[PDB]
Image (cartoon, rainbow over all chains, first blue to last red; front, side):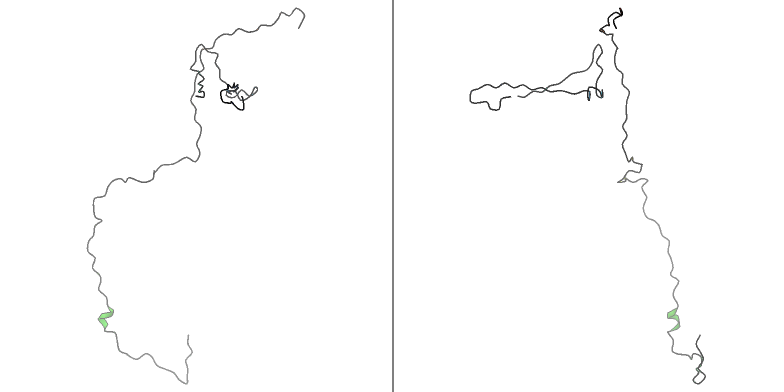
Length: 49
Length: 84
């Protein structure tokens, strides 16, 4: 992200989020089984206005 | 358990003026019949519950199912032609 956007300039942000379901790559606690024909599974994302 | 003085003995009690003998005799106080008054209600809107409570909370569960289990496209191994 730029530290200062001047008067009449454009800045470009980039950000990564890891949304955890399982606790780690070895401890599979919190993981979900999704190998199904259909599911009530969604991911709601609110963004900055 | 006093010791008798032989030089100065004394006799028994003599009569003295008295306290008007009926005024030391009481009346026997005469109780009338009584009643716990009113018609009593059968129940009371109590400020505390009358049953037991629990010290700790225990986690409860309910069973759920998974879904229709599908097949898969496996990555399949190579043929053991004496390299493996």
